[PDB]
Image (tube, helix red, strand yellow):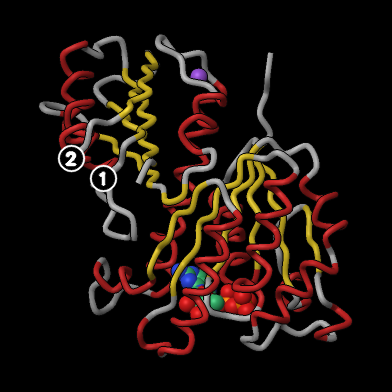
Amino acid sequence: SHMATLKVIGVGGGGNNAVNRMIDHGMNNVEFIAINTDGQALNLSKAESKIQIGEKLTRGLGAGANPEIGKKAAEESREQIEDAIQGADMVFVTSGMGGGTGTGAAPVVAKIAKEMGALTVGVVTRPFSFEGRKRQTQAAAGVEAMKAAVDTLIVIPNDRLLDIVDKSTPMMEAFKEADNVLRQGVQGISDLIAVSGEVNLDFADVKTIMSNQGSALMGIGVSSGENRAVEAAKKAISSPLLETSIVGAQGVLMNITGGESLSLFEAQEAADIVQDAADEDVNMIFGTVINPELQDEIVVTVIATGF
Ligand SMILES: Nc1nc2c(ncn2[C@@H]2O[C@H](COP(=O)(O)OP(=O)(O)O)[C@@H](O)[C@H]2O)c(=O)[nH]1
Ligand code: NA
């Protein structure tokens, strides 16, 4: 009856890098919008919809690390941004904080989406410490601005990438790991919408957990064999890349997908992992999907808010 329209918007260089790598990976039923001052980068964007902002301000260059330029470029193009969003039920705005375009334009894009009624989720990075204190300070101002403009915000400090690489891991492979946070969040919501689960969750449940909330965690875990439900739930709530951990979550959207062997006992085990890890009484919105194609595998999806 209702088919929710999801859009992913990349703002500035890193945000548009994320959009390009996600399109390359493959994502059906999601629409991508690339927003940048940098016309050279936009010409290389794989996104179906591209918006060059601030051409008269920047003559087609980036914003040169000045967030005021990004902010003015986005406001001067509000109509174009609204046209690109129109029809969206949910908008993911992804951006690297600390530069000129993302820091200044991403909060404007999010505000536009929110006042179009879209469930608006920000997924943003903080700069590496080696990029210096000014960049960290600019980024912090952009994070605060994003928080004021979105329904829910996921922050990925780039410094956490240094916790998951070895000395040889290519930087592009590290960036793909940060990409997965957004990509797997979008996909879990897309999967939730597409299927009528045995205990069904739908977009209105996503809205209940994410609307007007603040910090969020999105995660997915997949496991097989003995103890699969516990292991998958631990993976879903344990990202080394997130600023916001599960601890102190008070609302959780949790979906469990399994084959016909999905037992009541292990659904409780998985739910209990999330309750006990949050260390709070969690308002859980719980769903289950029996996908008989799956054999021994189980999938746990978690969206946590209420901090
Ligand atoms: N994780 C990740 N971070 C990025 C990427 N590109 C840029 N960044 C970070 O994002 C910050 C802003 O850079 P960028 O998006 O290119 O600046 P902007 O285009 O002016 O908004 C940089 O300081 C880096 O910390 C990326 O592809 N992945
Ligand atoms: Na569903």
Position of residue 193 measured from the top left corner of the image (x, y, whole percent) = 56, 25
Residue type at mark 2?
Asp
- Assess whether mark 2 and mark 1 are in contact (beta carbons under 8 angstroms): yes
Q: Is residue 130 left or right of residue 94?
A: left
Q: Earlier in the sequence, mark 1 or mark 2?
A: 1
User: Which residue is pictured at 61% across the width and 86% down the height?
Assistant: 65
Mark 1 neighbour class, 10 Å CA radius: few under 14, some 14 to 19, many 20 or more = some
**The N terminus: image quadrant:** top right
Query: Disc number at residue 34?
Result: none
| Relative vertical location of residue 255 with respect to residue 218 in this rendering, above or below | above
Image quadrant of residue 274? top left
- Neighbor class of circle 2 (other Cα within 10 Å; few <14, some 14-19, many 20+) is few
Q: Which residue is mark 2?
A: 279
Q: Residue at x 56, y 70 (%)?
A: 14
**SS at circle 1:** loop
In the rendered view, tell whether residue 263 sits above or below residue 143.
above
Question: Which image quadrant for residue 228?
Answer: top left
Question: In x, y percent, where is residue 211?
Answer: 54, 38
Q: Position of residue 225 (x, y in %)?
A: 15, 27
According to the image, label 1 marks what residue?
248
Q: Position of residue 31 (x, y in %)?
A: 69, 44
Secondary structure category for the residue under label 2:
loop
The one of 61 and 79 positioned closer to us in this rendering: 79
Q: From this view, report whether residue 160 is shown above or below residue 293.
A: below
Mark 1 is on which residue type?
Gly
Residue at image position (31%, 31%) is 300
